[PDB]
Image (cartoon, coloured by chain):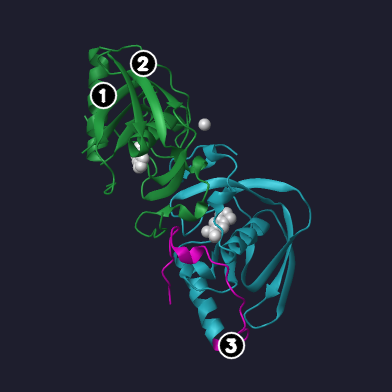
Chain colours: A green, B cyan
């Protein structure tokens, strides 16, 4: 079932989400399923549960839009926790299904570890770098009430997608 | 003649505009006329020349949309210069025809003087306060390559117009 993606300005994107406590359940598998399918219909590369107004520490991401980017595995991750593996920052283009039509260059950690659980309950623990890492940090921000504009350093790079010609 | 309003991301909104040097001319009266009419068709309260891709220190503003706001006189102002008359800041909702659908709360000086010229060449010099002042500061920012997002302090207040329920 495709869910409506709520848009920036909705207070429900600004909340700190509680943990998932129904790992391995049918209610969670169905919700995850709705997320992949919502993500897929909107052509997303990641989608966090608060963007479909579900107050939970859950995100889906991955794909084989962002045309220059390498493959990221299709992943559903509950209770994500993130640690930087280096202090190196890297600038890159982000957009967001809750902020349609726009994008900006955003600094993120180049190198992270993230941990949490698959919907079935098995542990997930990975080192990620570059675009993979950026996606996870971006979706993690939603789980703590944060959107990408408040991370923009260079406002010359923020603009509509069809108009932007800033050269990174 | 209504002109296309160019959208955030166009590099032409990011330039420092040179002065108008054709005060009292027919070329300027016609351009001003195009601005009022462009402003009017888009339901603006102010429009700066760089938003129709004209690289000049010129803006029009005023009206008898922003439904709670008091009347501001219809004004065409060339070579605007602005001085704060007090250090008092005041927060208020802004939007922008180059950033359609969005708005944010933005701090501005409560009390300003602005000077420059009418299109006919006569001097204009006024003290302005509140909404009047905010409009002029906002349009002045365009003339130096600046848009309102880079002035947002509280990102919880930035969002789409039809969705926002932040209570100022
Ligand atoms: O969640 C999203 O919509 C999103 C995350 C990232 S990272 C680069 C683009 C992009 N879009
Ligand atoms: O130039 C504009 O579109 C504009 C200036 C201001 S001040 C409050 C709204 C608003 N809109
Ligand atoms: Na918040
Ligand atoms: Na600029």
Label 2 lies in ligand 1 vicinity (Cβ under 8 Å): no
Relative horizontal placement of residue A73, taking residue B92 as reference (left or right): left
- The quadrant the N terminus of chain A occupies is top left
Q: Which of the marked residues, 1 or 2, is nearer the chain's N terminus?
A: 2
Question: What residue appears at the point 38 percent right and 44 percent down from the top-left corner?
Answer: A95
Secondary element under disc 3, as helix, strand or loop, is: loop
Question: What residue appears at the point 35 percent right and 11 percent down from the top-left corner?
Answer: A21
Q: For the residues carrying marks 3 and 2, which lies nearer the camera in this image? A: 2
- The quadrant the C terminus of chain A occupies is bottom left
| Residue receiving disc 1 | A32
**Most frequent secondary structure within the magenta stretch:** loop
Label 1 environment density (alpha carbons within 10 Å; few <14, some 14–19, many ≥20): many
- Say which chain tag 1 marks: A
Q: Are marks 3 and 1 on the same chain?
A: no
Tell which quarter ligand 4 is in.
Answer: bottom right
Question: What residue appears at the point 62 percent right and 76 percent down from the top-left corner?
Answer: B19
What span is colored magenta in the figure?
A: B1-26
Say if mark 3 contacts mark 1, CB within 8 Å.
no
Residue B158: percent from left, percent from top: 51, 43
Q: For the residues carrying marks 3 and 1, which lies nearer the camera in this image? A: 1
Secondary element under disc 2, as helix, strand or loop, is: loop
Queried whether the magenta region covers residue B11, the answer comes back as yes
Instruction: Identify which residue, A102 or B128, lies in the foreground.
Output: A102
- Say which chain tag 3 marks: B
On the image, which quarter does residue B79 sit in? bottom right
Question: What residue appears at the point 51 percent right and 82 percent down from the top-left corner?
Answer: B30
Residue A130: percent from left, percent from top: 36, 38
Q: In the figure, A74 relative to A102: above or below?
A: above
Queried whether the magenta region covers residue B129, the answer comes back as no
| Residue receiving disc 2 | A20
Q: Are marks 3 and 2 on the same chain?
A: no
């Amino acid at each position: 079932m495709i869910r409506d993606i709520i848009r920036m300005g909705d207070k429900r994107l600004l909340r700190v989400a509680p943990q998932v406590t129904n790992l391995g359940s049918a209610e969670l598998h169905a919700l995850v399923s709705d997320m992949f399918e919502t993500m897929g219909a909107a052509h997303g590369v990641g989608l966090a549960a608060p963007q479909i107004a579900v107050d939970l520490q859950l995100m889906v991401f991955g794909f084989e839009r962002y045309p220059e980017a390498p493959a990221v595995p299709l992943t559903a991750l509950a209770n994500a926790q993130i640690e930087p593996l280096s202090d190196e920052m890297e600038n890159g283009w982000e957009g967001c299904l809750s902020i349609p039509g726009l994008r900006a260059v955003i600094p993120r950690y180049r190198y992270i570890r993230y941990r949490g659980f698959a919907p079935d309950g098995s542990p997930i623990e990975r080192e990620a770098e570059g675009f993979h890492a950026r996606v996870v940090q971006h979706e993690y921000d939603h789980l703590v009430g944060r959107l990408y504009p408040s991370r923009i350093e260079n406002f010359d790079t923020f603009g509509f997608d069809d108009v932007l010609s800033y050269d990174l």
